[PDB]
Image (spheres, coloured by chain):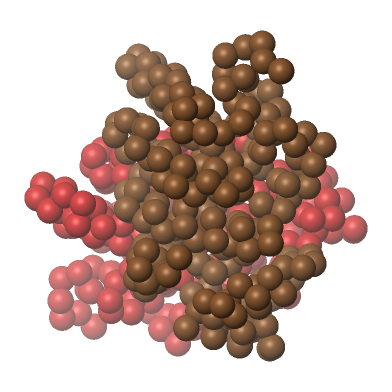
Chain colours: A brown, B red
Amino acid sequence: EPADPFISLLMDPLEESVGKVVNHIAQLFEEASKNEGDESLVLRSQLGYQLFFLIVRSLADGKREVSKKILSGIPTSVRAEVFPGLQRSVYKSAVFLGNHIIQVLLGEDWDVVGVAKDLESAWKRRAIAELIKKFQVSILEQCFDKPVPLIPQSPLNNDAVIDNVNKALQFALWLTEFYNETEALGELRFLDSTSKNLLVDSFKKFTHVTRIVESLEK
Amino acid sequence: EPADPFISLLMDPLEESVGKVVNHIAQLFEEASKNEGDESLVLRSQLGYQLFFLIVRSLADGKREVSKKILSGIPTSVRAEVFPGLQRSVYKSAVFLGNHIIQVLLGEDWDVVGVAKDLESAWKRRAIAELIKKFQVSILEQCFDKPVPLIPQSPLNNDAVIDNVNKALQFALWLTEFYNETEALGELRFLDSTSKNLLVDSFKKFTHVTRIVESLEK
């Protein structure tokens, strides 16, 4: 049920609604940059995290190409701050990897999309990790002062959804930061249920697979 | 024993040597930015991480004010990328907190230095966390293609030192990201030895203390 602009636009996601929200956040960001310098920048932090909230939202509802459309609707000046440095270059792989892991937890070829080649680079790895991190704390913290469901029309299951997505992004971070060591294995104690079998089933159809199947048995 | 410029400058730290190294990294970064655009930026990633390596080095040898001097010897254009957004504003608190935890693990008033007020802000928290993260993976990854000791004149104990400092920064990250919950407690399984008692002894002299002493007993 609508009443305000932004809150009504924050409901169901499509190219239209999502695009509107993005542009209109980019406005706050824009005139922030046009006037109040560093203070404005401090605002731009939270604003960017709202953008990341939109991205994660696009990841959870199975709308990955929309997550890719997020980057297009953002001014380059804004993009320079929100995705600083190498982050803007590996954004595609971050979105792809995140979407893959998230959808796996919920229940394309990596070399073709260019994810593997990005994982070969340690710096691109770290950038991807930064982005996935941002994805995580974008739904962890209160981007909006008014609580808005990560998935529209699912208010009661909001904390469940958020916890799940968070754990998914956590395992993605594990993948990036540990691209079967003992120390690496100690960081898998976070898992709850169903996840391991989902890894098995997903990587069965898809040498990352090898490394993970090796890690699990240890 | 010296032979090259950079490698010889990468030895013992003082205002002179450290300053030289910083300026000279800032040169590579500079002419990178002056020509090869995005590729240059990709270089600027690793370069910035070398800068962070210098910062961590300044944290480990008990030279915190030098870590603060790092920021001064860096061009603003470079600073915009290396410390993007709110990171440049909370850099002081990141350096301070990191130094505190590191020196505690090895064996000033927080409200006065402004750390507590920064921890009150979730976005400043996240920024600090990003910086500490960068500190961690700056010593985790090979910033220089030639291995250079984190602490000069300590080559054999290099991996020991690195592991220790890494764990310190890890606990700092725990402090930032969990500013006595069950889920929060599960993230304390990383501890090895001596650390808990160091927390006790350090916070005994120093309501963060309260929250930690509460967490430990649970």
Image quadrant for the C terminus of chain B? bottom right
Image location (x, y in percent) of residue A190? 73, 65
Whether residue B76 can be seen here: yes
Left or right: B86 with respect to B201?
left
Which residue is painted at 20% across and 79% down in the image? B2
Could you tell whether B211 is left or right of A125 in the image? right
In percent of the image, x 79 and y 67: which residue is there? Answer: A193
Q: Is residue B206 left or right of residue B75?
A: right
Number of marks drawn: 0
Residue A89 drawn above or below residue B193: above
Of residue A70 and residue B17, the one placed in the foreground of this image is A70
Kindly give the residue lying farthest to the left in the view shown: B35
| Residue B21 placement, left or right of A175 | left
Identify the residue at image location x=35%, y=68%: A112
Q: Nearer the viewer, residue A181 or B69?
A: A181
The quarter of the displayed image where residue A31 is located: top left
Q: Residue at x 77, y 68 (%)?
A: A194
**Where is residue B91 shown, x and y percent of the image?**
46, 42
Image quadrant assignment for residue A39: top left
Note whether A147 is above or below A49 in the view shown: above
Residue B108: horizontal and vertical position, in percent?
60, 43
Q: Residue B156 or A188: which is nearer the viewer?
A: A188
Residue A208 at x, y = what percent? Answer: 50, 79
Which quadrant does the N terminus of chain B fall into?
A: bottom left
- Picture quadrant of residue A185: bottom right
Residue A42 in view: no
